[PDB]
Structures are given as structure tokens and as C-alpha cells.
Image (cartoon, rainbow, N blue to C red):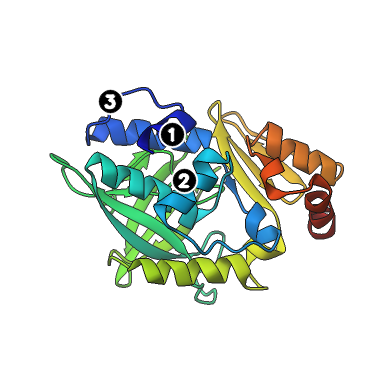
Amino acid sequence: DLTGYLDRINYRGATDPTLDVLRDLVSAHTGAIAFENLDPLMGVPVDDLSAEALADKLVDRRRGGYCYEHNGLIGYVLAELGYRVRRLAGRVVWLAPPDAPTPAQTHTVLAVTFPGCQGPYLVDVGFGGMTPTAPLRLETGTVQQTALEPYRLDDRGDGLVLQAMVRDEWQALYEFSTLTRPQVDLRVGSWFVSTHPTSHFVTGLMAATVADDARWNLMGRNLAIHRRGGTEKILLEDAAAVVDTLGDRFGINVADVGERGRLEARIDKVCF
């Protein structure tokens, strides 16, 4: 199934486990497979994090997914190619002040090593809205410029916090432990975020992708295109326009979700 995935992300290069290949895979993945939560929005949990289920959805069915699906899938691919992959858990703190409540531990990211690596790399292709489109050195202090924003890791408690300069302010994105977590713990987290009535992935629509040096971010009916030069904001007119945008700009096979009218009705209720 390695080839199905590589075709899905339009990847052409070498497949040896090197830093160059990791960079090129991460760039290809993040440009090809959207972040989206249409399953949880429609009452379909994200419960099966196996390679086969994630490939069937994100590759064969041309859907996107959220963190567990993205980092699930790329993690399996990287391991098949000969990288060593450890799955980590984190808490999302984006836009939160330092005195905010402790968030649930419902993000997942990867620590990746390979022959000749100078150290481990953080890979996260699943953090919709702000996901780094390059592997990042798992090291604190260093400012790490990507094709988009600069990122930086710092020590926090008995773990790390990933930050990015967004527009003109350094913003903490998520905090994470560098301890490997078992697959079952990731499943418990994904169940919560895909089914809990308070989950932002159950109560609203979120989609994200990257195209032409720009982030395309959709929160409900609110589309934002963050380009180098600035940000364009568009208010989508109705649920039909939102579905058209998911298919046309985010590359999602929205037909997979079922009857277009049922998707539109949910979007109408939630987003309008």
C-alpha cells in the first residue's frame, strides 16, 4: 500500500530513510491530504487507527482526517520505509493564556529517527490550522524556519511546547511529553475528541490545507487564506458553498460522507 499512499500525495522522489526524503514526504503529505473533521461532525467516530482503516479512508477514499488519522498514517508509512517512529501525546493550547485550564491530552505527534540523523525529529502533519510542513529538529531554543511560519520548541514542565510565530506573535500551539504512548491510549484520546459533546471537532466544522505558500483554513463558514503578503477572509454564503469549498479547495471526496443533503443539513445547523 506504500505506492497507493505515495500516489495520493503525488510524491516522486527517493524512498530511502533520509532527512531529505522525510522533508519531501512531509511537504507532499501536507499539500495533498486535508485536515478535516467531517466524520465526527456527522456522528461517525474516529475509533479505528489501524494502518488499513486509515489508508482506506485517507488514501483510497480521498478523504482527509484529523491528528490521529494524519499522524497515524504517516507514522505507518515512515516505519515501513525504515524510519524509527515513536508516537507521542500532547495537549492543545493554541491561543490559550498561561492560566487556562489543563486541556485533554488529545493531540498526537511523532518522534522520528533514521540512519545518520543528528538527533530525533518532530513530525506533525495532523495539527490543522498550523501544522508544521517540515520535520523539526527535536531540540529546544532553535528557531526553525519552514516554508510557512517559523517554529520553536521549548522546555515546559516534564515535556515540551511547540510554538510558532503566527502573523507577528509567538504562539504556543501544544505541549507534549516525549514519552512513547501505547496505541490504546491514542484510541482513547481519539474516541474522546471524535465523540464527546464538548469536543470542538464534534460541535463545529474545521478544515485546513496548504497551497501556493498559503494556509487555507476553514472554521465553519469562515474561510481564511493566509498568504505571505497577508490574510484574505471570506464568509461563505450557505451550506452548499461550504460543501463546494470542501470538495473544490480542500480536495475532499465529500460524496464519501453520504447524501449531500444530509451533510448540508448538518453544516447548516452547526455552521449557520
Image quarter for residue 147? top left
Write down the residue under mark 3.
14
Write down the residue under mark 1.
4
Give me the residue at 22% from left, 42% from top: 82
Residue 126 visible within the image: no
What whole-number distance in Å separates the C-alpha atoms at marks 2 and 3?
21 Å
Q: Which mark, by number, is residue 148?
A: none
Give me the residue at 50% from left, 33% from top: 31
Residue nearer the viewer, 124 or 100: 124
CB within 8 Å, label 1 to label 2: yes
Sequence-earlier tag: 1 or 2: 1
Q: Is residue 231 above or below residue 84?
A: above
Place of residue 208 in the rendered image (x, y in percent of width and height, measured from the top left): 60, 43
Give me the residue at 59% from left, 65% from top: 194
Place of residue 62 in the rendered image (x, y in percent of width and height, measured from the top left): 57, 38
Place of residue 81 in the rendered image (x, y in percent of width and height, measured from the top left): 26, 39
Q: Secondary structure at mark 1?
A: helix
Residue type (three-letter) at the residue carrying disc 3 = Ala
Place of residue 94 in the rendered image (x, y in percent of width and height, measured from the top left): 53, 59
What whole-number distance in Å separates the C-alpha atoms at marks 1 and 2?
9 Å
Image quarter for residue 223? top right
Of the 4 image quadrants, the one containing the N terminus is: top left
Residue type (three-letter) at the residue carrying disc 1 = Gly
Sequence-earlier tag: 2 or 3: 3
Q: Is residue 144 above or below residue 45?
A: above
Q: Which mark, by number, is residue 55?
A: 2
Give me the residue at 45% from left, 59% from top: 49
Sequence-earlier tag: 1 or 3: 1
Residue type (three-letter) at the residue carrying disc 2 = Ala
